[PDB]
Image 1 (cartoon, rainbow, N blue to C red):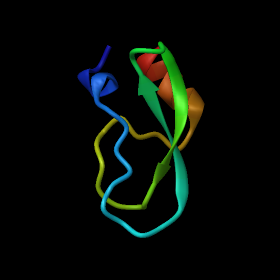
Image 2: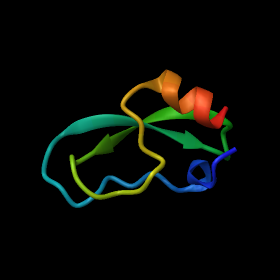
Image 3: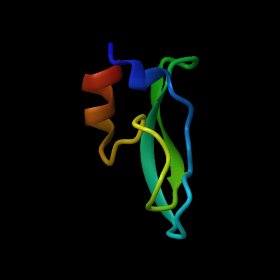
Image 4: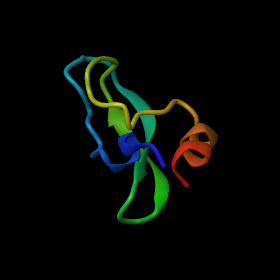
Length: 56
């Protein structure tokens, strides 16, 4: 279990209106969150399955 999975959701510094997946270790599930296209942290995936095989 990569330590990136413990990181909190981070929308970032950018200006785009996008959606990404991050592993919420508290709820034990890969959830959706708003991303700006730049910045943030490693707990950021474009596909839910990738978040699951990495963190669940």
